[PDB]
Amino acid sequence: DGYFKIYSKHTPINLVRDLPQGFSALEPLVDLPIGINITRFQTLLALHR
Amino acid sequence: SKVGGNYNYLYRLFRKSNLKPFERDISTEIYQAGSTPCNGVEGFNCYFP
Image 1 (tube, rainbow over the protein chains, first blue to last red):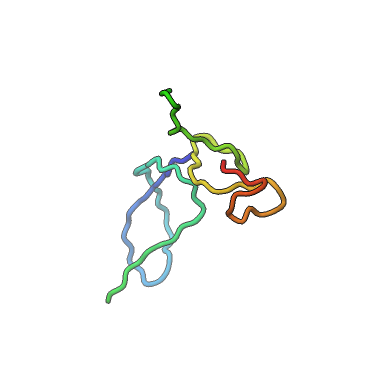
Image 2: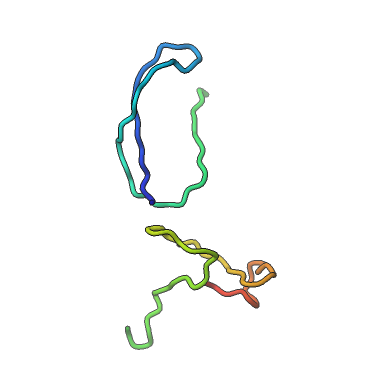
């Protein structure tokens, strides 16, 4: 219905390459009514020269 | 309603489907009503919505 719902939570970790076993929830943060039809997305990163 | 008429109001006549509540449609193109592609040029069975 146009509304863009976003949740989040922050937590550190001490690991090399894995996903640790445990439990943690998420909470609502912010909602904006952009209201555009959406069917795709991508992602941007950074590089060190 | 001025003398000579006001023509700053436009609306879409032809569409390929129905809309959803609280959703907009602003992009414009040509509409084909027959079995021949319009080829981007106004012709028979080719009308601006």
